[PDB]
Image (cartoon, rainbow over all chains, first blue to last red; front, side, top):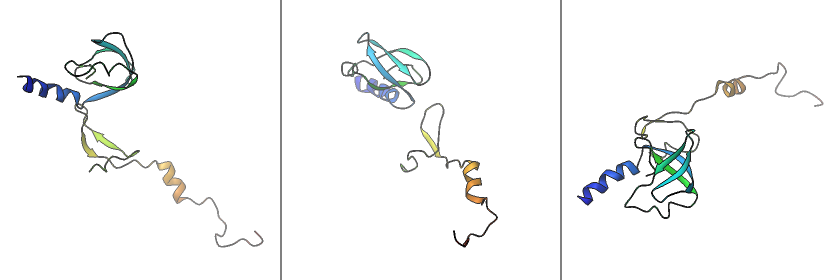
Length: 70
Length: 51
């Protein structure tokens, strides 16, 4: 079941994606980022994959269907 | 090909899944096309003496 579940997330990690810039972390759970779409977002950081090298300043991708930081 | 993407060329991508449906050949601005065809002169392009 774990192997079947991981499959499901990979699909989301992949396109469609919309790019942003990741400013800074206010929680390990959820973080604040800014898009190129003209919206500032509070987006959730995907679990059972690192969220602790997520935290520095970098370019980041957010999923189009789910509006999360995959 | 992966050569159907190179910086500055046009691409069509699907709206709902953002994967490449096709190559889209780049637009040619009509303004550049006018500059290529037209010669603003009405004088010889061989020589003008003393020039």
